[PDB]
Image (cartoon, rainbow, N blue to C red):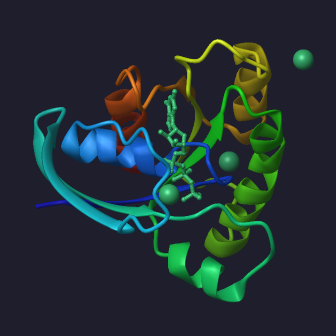
Amino acid sequence: MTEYKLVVVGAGGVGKSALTIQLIQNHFVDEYDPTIEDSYRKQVVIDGETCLLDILDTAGQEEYSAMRDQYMRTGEGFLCVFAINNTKSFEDIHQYREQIKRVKDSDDVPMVLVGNKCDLAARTVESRQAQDLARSYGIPYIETSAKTRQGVEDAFYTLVREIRQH
Ligand SMILES: Nc1nc2c(ncn2[C@@H]2O[C@H](COP(=O)(O)OP(=O)(O)NP(=O)(O)O)[C@@H](O)[C@H]2O)c(=O)[nH]1
Ligand SMILES: [Ca+2]
Ligand SMILES: [Mg+2]
Ligand code: NA
């Protein structure tokens, strides 16, 4: 049974955990909880293949860290998450994608750019801006809401599909 090793990265507070817990357990964590387990497992059927997701939910990262690079370098694909109402988090994406490229030693890494919190009205990152950023990386852009479930499955399943192309 194939296992897909996914890693969730991005700035603090963008909804990495909320996305992963919505995916795995169908619950929205509406309260920012600072001790949430990093590892998740789920058996799912994706395009007719019964498979295991092994998801590593990481933290935001402000400063370079060799142990953080090591913790995430065995991912097969990466969800690079920002929030649509957090310009900073969007601008921070390129540090995360550089870290991915450094750890995989490649510019051809399975990856999905996720614009989370799409339910919220205070949008400061336009869809076009993110589409463009994603296009510059050669990856898809998908908007999600961990609160409403919009795009959540899509983002994770898209990442599996990208891993399958690699
Ligand atoms: N409205 C809304 N709020 C959300 C969404 N996703 C996350 N949140 C909220 O944003 C806050 C942070 O979410 P959380 O998942 O803890 O962020 P994180 O990226 O895992 N933070 P960290 O890197 O510090 O571990 C929580 O209050 C959460 O409820 C969303 O799609 N919509
Ligand atoms: Ca603007
Ligand atoms: Mg978290
Ligand atoms: Na790339």
Q: Is residue 74 left or right of residue 46?
A: right
Res 130 → quadrant: top right
Relative height, residue 1 to residue 80 (above, below): below
The residue at 64%/78% (across/down) is 69
Quadrant where the N terminus lies?
bottom left
Q: Position of residue 38 (x, y in %)?
A: 39, 68
From the top left corner, tell me how far across and down residue 114 is, in percent. 57, 35
Q: Is residue 165 visible?
A: no
Q: Residue at x 57, y 64 (%)?
A: 59
**Lateral position of residue 71 relative to residue 147, left or right:** right
Residue 20 at what x, y percent from top left?
Answer: 37, 48
Q: Nearer the viewer, residue 136 or 147?
A: 147
User: In this rendering, does residue 87 appear at all?
Assistant: yes
Instruction: Say how many tags the image has.
Output: 0
Splitting the image into four quadrants, where does ligand 2 fall?
top right
Is 28 situated left or right of 43 in this image? right
In the image, farthest residue toward the front: 31
The furthest residue to the bottom: 67
Nearest the camera: 40 or 72?
A: 40
